[PDB]
Amino acid sequence: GSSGSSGSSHLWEFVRDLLLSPEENCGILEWEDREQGIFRVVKSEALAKMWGQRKKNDRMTYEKLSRALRYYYKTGILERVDRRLVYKFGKNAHGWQEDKLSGPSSG
């Protein structure tokens, strides 16, 4: 059977899905680099507002959302950038990445 149930939600996933779902996302993000996976948050306000709705957090706002954007750097899910309102999915994240690139080294 197939439906589409994960069980554990995640911001990095929500914000990412928006990039692959132009039908739901309304000029909220931008694809700075498809290969690298870098994206920009054109609407830092709409980004959070929409996020909260997913977590039923009426008090959801960028200031708060970021909390997870900066906490992802520890796990690798996200990649710290030296730009403004510009984030990039690390290697820990999946779905956005393309092609099969591992490297000359392996375990």
Image: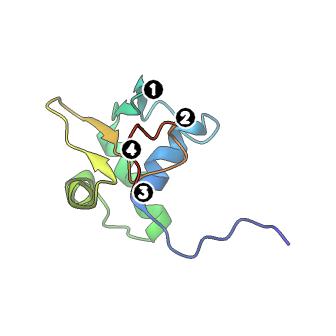
Q: Earlier in the sequence, mark 4 or mark 3?
A: 4
Which residue is at 67% across, 71% downward? 5
Q: Nearer the viewer, residue 87 or 46?
A: 87
Residue marked by disc 2:
98
Q: Earlier in the sequence, mark 1 or mark 2?
A: 1
Q: CA distance from mark 4 to mark 3?
A: 8 Å
**At label 1, which amino acid type do we have?**
Glu
Q: Residues within 10 Å of mark 1 (few under 14, many from 20)?
A: few
Residue 51: numbered disc: 3
**At label 4, which amino acid type do we have?**
Ala
Q: Residues within 10 Å of mark 3 (few under 14, many from 20)?
A: many
Which residue is at 17% across, 29% downward? 83
Q: Are marks 4 and 3 in contact (CB under 8 Å)?
A: no
Q: Are marks 1 and 2 in contact (CB under 8 Å)?
A: yes
**Can you tell which quarter of the image residue 88 is in?**
top left
Element assignment for label 1:
loop
**At label 3, which amino acid type do we have?**
Trp
Residue marked by disc 4:
46
Q: Count the labels in the image.
A: 4
User: In screen coordinates, is 85 left or right of 48?
Assistant: left
Q: Are marks 1 and 3 in contact (CB under 8 Å)?
A: no
Q: CA distance from mark 4 to mark 2?
A: 27 Å
Quadrant into which the N terminus falls: bottom right
Residue marked by disc 1:
35
Q: Are marks 2 and 3 in contact (CB under 8 Å)?
A: no
